[PDB]
Image (tube, rainbow, N blue to C red):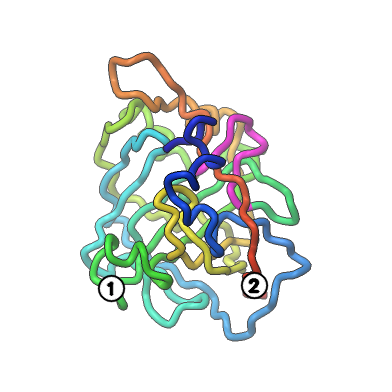
Amino acid sequence: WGYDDKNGPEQWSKLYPIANGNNQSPVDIKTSETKHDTSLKPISVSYNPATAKEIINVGHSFHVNFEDNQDRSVLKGGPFSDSYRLFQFHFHWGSTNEHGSEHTVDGVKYSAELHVAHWNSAKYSSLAEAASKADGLAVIGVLMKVGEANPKLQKVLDALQAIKTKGKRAPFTNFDPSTLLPSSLDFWTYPGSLTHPPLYESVTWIICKESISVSSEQLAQFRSLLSNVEGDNAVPMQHNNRPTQPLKGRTVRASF
Ligand SMILES: [Zn+2]
């Protein structure tokens, strides 16, 4: 599967019928229809920089993975009653610098999107197992607005020089992803899914109200990564964002 048109979002259902599921992500957040839940608690992230482990080119994107054998780095609060263990952060972007986020707000597509994913360590034993359960995953989505360069992205950008092609991995340590999050962590939340195959509807989304910046040349760097394996002709990672899916009667709750 991919993002091109032969194997892209509009073709995924042919292989993953859940693509047409009732809790698909991303979604358009219509700020006027959001429900303020007074039961929501502020989200509390507590990550240990020593759990940062590797950066890897997965072809369609790059992942920054973390050690997930303990509760050193967790997400708590929000709509949760238990702790979610951090396992990874990655991004989404588009072919253009101004339209590449997954989630949209009031129909407005942002330049890129940051996803911080965690799995339900309390109810399940492994990411593998939790990945398909309704309460399995918790993902923080942060909208990125093209503008001023974001200096907090530099270690990630620098690391990309070592994983130019698919399957390349490089150690990526001592990084606390909470440094990528906005100032305020007011959020929107809804039950949804993974935004690409397997498309499991196992995610509890936390979309930060506040966006963060990125510059044009910072995004050009992501698109400079290669989807091919070393040695083959160059095939740029031009985009990896999935179009918004019907809400299908879900409610987006707000922290405020
Ligand atoms: Zn993602």
- Residue 22 in magenta stretch: no
Residue 218 can be seen in this image: no
Residue 202 can be seen in this image: yes
Image quarter hosting the N terminus: top left
Q: In the image shown, does 212 or 111 lie closer to the viewer?
A: 111
Q: Secondary structure at mark 2?
A: loop
Amino acid carrying mark 2 in the image: Thr
Point 37% across, 44% down: residue: 63
Q: Is residue 132 above or below residue 107?
A: below
- Residue 98 in magenta stretch: yes
Q: Start and end of the magenta stretch?
A: 92-103
Residue 92 locus on image (x, y percent): 51, 43
Q: Quadrant of residue 110?
A: top right
Residue under label 1, please give it.
Answer: 124
Q: Quadrant of residue 124?
A: bottom left
Magenta stretch secondary structure, dominant: loop
Q: Quadrant of residue 256?
A: bottom right
Q: Residues within 10 Å of mark 2 (few under 14, many from 20)?
A: some
Residue under label 2, please give it.
Answer: 251
Point 54% across, 31% down: residue: 5
Q: Is residue 164 above or below residue 255?
A: above
